[PDB]
C-alpha cells in the first residue's frame, strides 16, 4: 500500500508537470495560469481517484470532494504554488502534493517541472531529490543563518513586527520563491524560512519533505503545523517557520514572540 | 569581425557554464562560489584574449587588464551575478558578458547555465533566447506593471524613498533574482525592473539585450547608462530602471524624482 501511494503520487506529479509546461511562458502579449492550474489539478485528481476511489481530494477551487461522507486518506494539492512567479516567467513555482492519513501528512512532493527537480518526503524514509537522499545542514547561531521568505509585503499587522525581529538577526534575508525555498532548506542550502499567510495546500506537502531531511517545521508558536482536511475544514492561512537546525528554530521562535 | 565577436562570446559562455555547473550546489555542509567565479572568469578571458590579443578585459577582482596601454574593445565580465542565489542553491544567478567598442556595449549575453537559457543582444539584431527572437510587451500604465527588484534591502538613503514612490504605484512588486529579471523583461514577462547599486559588470551586458528586445534601460534620471571601461575607470555603482514599454519607463522616471 505505501509504495503504491508513492507510485500514484509520482504519476500525478508527472501529469501535472506536462500540463504546466504547456502553459508556462505563453503569456508574453481565462489566463494561461488559471487554465494550467485547473487542468493540472484535474489530471492529478483523475489518477489519484482512479487508483483510490475511497480517498478524498482537497483543492483551492473545489474544496473537499469525496464520493463518501468521510475518508481516512485525503490528498491536498496545489498545482501552482507561486502564481506570481509563474505569471512572470520565473521557473521557481512548484507543484505540491500531500497525502494525509487521519489528518497527518504521510507523503509530500515538491515538484519544479521546468527544472525537473522533485523532492519527495515519505514517512519512514529519508527525503530524496530526484531519487538521491538529501539532508539539512547545521547552523551555529541565528546570526549565521541564511533566511528566505517570499516577499516583504506578505506580512500584515503584528506578523510584520514579528518577522522584522527575526529578519534583523539573521545573516541575510533573501526573497522571492515560495515553496522552492523549503526545498533548498531540505537540501541544506538554506537555514531558515519564515512566512505568514500560507494556505494548507501550500504547506502540508512541505512537512514530510523537511522533517525527512532532518529539519524542523512548525507554526510561529512552535506547535505542530496541522490542518485536518475534512468536509468542514476551513482553508485559512497559517504562519510557518522552518529551519535546517533545531537550535536555530528555537532562536527564531524566541524572536517571533508569537 | 562582428559575427566573430558573437562566436567568441558564446565560446566564453560555454566555458563559464561548465565551470559554474561543477561548483553549483556543492556547499551543503576558498568557498566554491569564489573558486567558481575565479575559474570561470579565467576560462572566459582565456578564450577572448586568445582570439583578440589587442582587446582589454575588465572584471571585479582584477580590474582593467590589457597588453597594451589602451584598447578600442573591452570585454566586461561577471561570471556570477547573483552570488547570494548561487550560495543558497537558487538557479537564477547569471553569467554576464559585455563587449564595448569605444565605451559603448555592442554585444551582451545573459547566461543561466543550470536552466540552459542564453539571451544574446547584438547591435543591429533582435535579441534572442536560445536562438529564437524575443520581444518586450506593451503595458498600459504603471498601475498595470509587474515590477522586479533583487531585494528591498538594497536601497539606501534617498534611493529608498525614490524606490518606494515607484513601488507603491505598480501592480505588484516582486523580488529576488538579479539579472534574471531583466532577461524576463526582454522576453515580455516583466514590465519594469528598478535597482540601485549595480556595478558596471552587472549592467552593461543588459543593455544590448533589453534594447534589442524593444525595451528601454537608463539611469534614474533617464540618461544613458554608460561606463567607459579604461585603465582609470572606477567601478562604482549605478541606479538602473528598465521597462518593456517606453511610456512606463517615463512614468517610472517621474515617480523616482531623481
Ligand atoms: Cl480506495
Ligand atoms: Cl586583436
Image: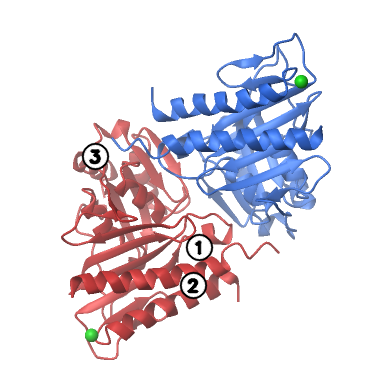
Chain colours: A red, B blue
Task: Provide residue A215's location: percent of width, then percent of height.
Answer: 23, 48
Q: Do discs 1 and 2 belong to a common subunit?
A: yes
Q: Which numbered disc covers residue A37?
A: 2
Which quarter holds ligand 1? bottom left
How many numbered circles are shown?
3
Secondary structure of residue under mark 3: helix
Residue located 29% across and 83% down the image: A51
Point out the tag, 3 or 1, that comes first from the N-terminus: 1
Q: Do discs 3 and 2 belong to a common subunit?
A: yes
Whole-Å distance between the Cαs marked 3 and 1?
30 Å
Q: Quadrant of residue B77?
A: top right
- Nearer the observer, B30 or A83: B30
> Please, which chain is the residue tagged with disc 3 on?
A
Residue located 40% across and 40% down the image: B88
**What is the crowding at mark 1: few (fewer than 14 residues within 10 Å), some, or many (at least 20)?**
some
> Please, which chain is the residue tagged with disc 2 on?
A
- Nearer the observer, A240 or A16: A16
Whole-Å distance between the Cαs marked 1 and 2?
9 Å
Q: Which residue is denoted by mark 3 in the rendering? A: A248
Q: Say above or below: B103 vs A27.
A: above
Q: Which residue is denoted by mark 1 in the rendering? A: A83
Amino acid at each position: 500500500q505505501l509504495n503504491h501511494f508513492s507510485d500514484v503520487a509520482n504519476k500525478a506529479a508527472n501529469a501535472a508537470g506536462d500540463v504546466i509546461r504547456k502553459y508556462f511562458r505563453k503569456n508574453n502579449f481565462l489566463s494561461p495560469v488559471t487554465i494550467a492550474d485547473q487542468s493540472a489539478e484535474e489530471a492529478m485528481v483523475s489518477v489519484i481517484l482512479d487508483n483510490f476511489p475511497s480517498h478524498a481530494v482537497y483543492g483551492e477551487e473545489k474544496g473537499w470532494r469525496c464520493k463518501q461522507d468521510s475518508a481516512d486518506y485525503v490528498w491536498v494539492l496545489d498545482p501552482i504554488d507561486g502564481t506570481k512567479s509563474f505569471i512572470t516567467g520565473k521557473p521557481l513555482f512548484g507543484t505540491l502534493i500531500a497525502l494525509l492519513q487521519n489528518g497527518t501528512p504521510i507523503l509530500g512532493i515538491i515538484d519544479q517541472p521546468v527544472l525537473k527537480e522533485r523532492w519527495i518526503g515519505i514517512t519512514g524514509k529519508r527525503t530524496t531529490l530526484n531519487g538521491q537522499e538529501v539532508s539539512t545542514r547545521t547552523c551555529a547561531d541565528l546570526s549565521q543563518a541564511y533566511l528566505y521568505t517570499t516577499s516583504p509585503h506578505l506580512f500584515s499587522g503584528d506578523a510584520e513586527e514579528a518577522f522584522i525581529r527575526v529578519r534583523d538577526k539573521v545573516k541575510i534575508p533573501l526573497y522571492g520563491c515560495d515553496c522552492y525555498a523549503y526545498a533548498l532548506l531540505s537540501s541544506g542550502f538554506v537555514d531558515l524560512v519564515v512566512e505568514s499567510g500560507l494556505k494548507p495546500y501550500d504547506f502540508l506537502a512541505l512537512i514530510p519533505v523537511i522533517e525527512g531531511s532532518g529539519g524542523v517545521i512548525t507554526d510561529w508558536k512552535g506547535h505542530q503545523l496541522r490542518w485536518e482536511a475534512s468536509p468542514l475544514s476551513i482553508a485559512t492561512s497559517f504562519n510557518v517557520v522552518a529551519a535546517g537546525d533545531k537550535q536555530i528554530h528555537q532562536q527564531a521562535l524566541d524572536s517571533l514572540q508569537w
